[PDB]
Structures are given as C-alpha cells and as structure tokens.
Length: 137
Image 1 (cartoon, rainbow, N blue to C red):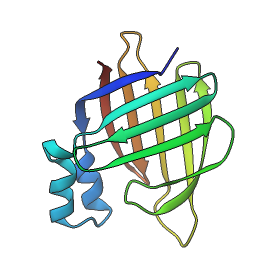
Image 2 (cartoon, rainbow, N blue to C red):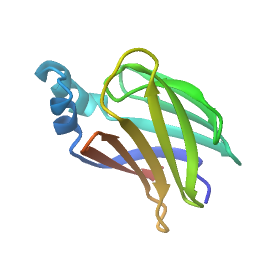
Image 3 (cartoon, helix red, strand yellow):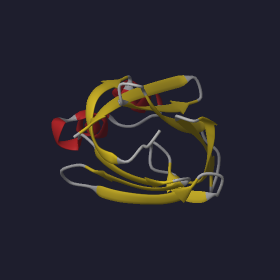
Image 4 (cartoon, one colour):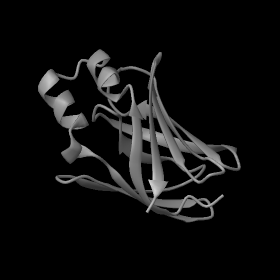
C-alpha cells in the first residue's frame, strides 16, 4: 500500500455536475473540465506523511500533511478549510474538511488504491459525489 507516484487521470465522473450544483458559473465549469485543466498528481508517501503536488497546464499547487494532523487547504470550490485525514483502511484515507470562515456544504474527499494499482479519488459535497481515477506513469 504505497501511494507514491506520478499519477495521470484516466476517468472522471460527475465533476462538472458537482460544480454546477455548487453554483460555479458555466465559463469556469467548462474550463475546469477542459483537456488543458486535466490534473497530473505527484505523490510522495513516507509512512503517514504525504506530499502531493497537483499540476495542470496553467496551475500548480502542493499540499503536505500527516495522517491524523490538521492542515489547511481549499474546498472543491476554492474556500479555505481546515482538513484532517484518517485511515479508513490500509489502502484508503478519508478527509473531513471544515470551513475557516462562514458556512457551506459538508465537504470531504477520499483517496484509495485498487489491487491493480489504480488511484481512486472521490470528493463529496452534501449529497453529491464526484469520482476520478488515475494510473501511474
């Protein structure tokens, strides 16, 4: 169960629709799903410590966290949040997010490995879920 690698996206389901129900305007949705916005995800895992860099043709962001320790990131629609990841199993982590300011949808995400070595990401806002699948280069 090692999440490290250079992960390339191979499936995406319900992402634009999730943004739509969050109130994201149509220009930004279409951009978010364009080929040019396809995420490449680099992960370095060392036990419970993660470094994850997500890059597209125009953006790059890095997060560093340790499982069980609170950190700060942004929600699917860009609002700052405090996050905390826990293991649900040997091969799956789950993250609960809490907005830093104001109120909003209950948001969370998960990452898990398949035995064939696919990485599955889900992101949830209230009752709406999006799933992306990646494979290693």
